[PDB]
Image 1 (cartoon, rainbow, N blue to C red):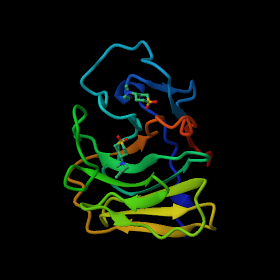
Image 2 (cartoon, helix red, strand yellow):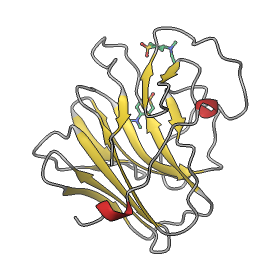
Image 3 (cartoon, rainbow, N blue to C red):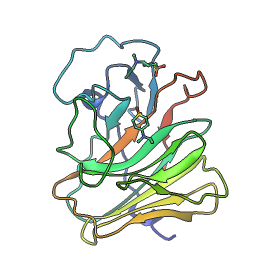
Image 4 (tube, helix red, strand yellow):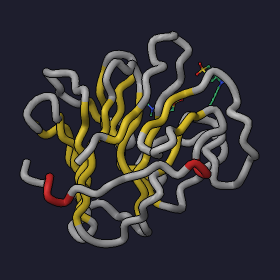
Length: 185
Ligand SMILES: CC#CCN(C)C1CCS(=O)(=O)CC1
Ligand SMILES: CC#CCN(C)C1CCS(=O)(=O)CC1
C-alpha cells in the first residue's frame, strides 16, 4: 500500500480506559494491570472489557496509523463511533459502531456480524489501519508481510465522529500480558 503519507500521531485517552489498564506517560502504550489501577469511575470508561479509545476524533479525510501486537495472544483493533456503548456486554460489529479485526484462540477474524475468517500466512507483529472517511472505508495491513492487505470494510456507515479503538484482551492464560504500542511515524 501507499497510505503512509496520511500518518497521524495517535495518543490514548486515559479517561476512556477500563480501570485495570495502564497507559504509559507518553500515552502511546497500554497494557492490562494485575488489579484495579486506583482511578475514579466515569461514564466514558469501558466497564466489561480491557478497552480504550484514542484521543483523536476524525470526521473527514484520510488517516493512517500502526500498532505493535508483538507476543500477544488476543487483541481487538480498529475504529469506532464516538457514541459506542461503554457499559455492559456488547459485540464488536458495524451495527454497534465498530470496524475492527482481532486475534483470538490462534485465529484472525474481522468484526462483521457474524465474524469473517481472515487468511494470514505471516502472523503480524505490527498492524496498519487506514480510514477514508468520505469513501466509507477501513482497511487493515500486515506490516510484517511487506504491507499486505488483511481486510477492507467498505460501504461503511460511520454515522458520527470516529475514534481509534483498542482492546488489549484478557490475560487468563498468563501469555497475554504484553502491551499494545502505537509505532512511531
Ligand atoms: C469470538 C471473539 C473475539 C475477539 N473479541 C471480539 C472479544 C472481545 C470481548 S473479550 O472479552 O475481550 C474477548 C475477545
Ligand atoms: C477488565 C476486566 C476484567 C475481568 N477481571 C476480573 C479479570 C481481569 C484480569 S484477567 O487476567 O484478564 C482475569 C479477569
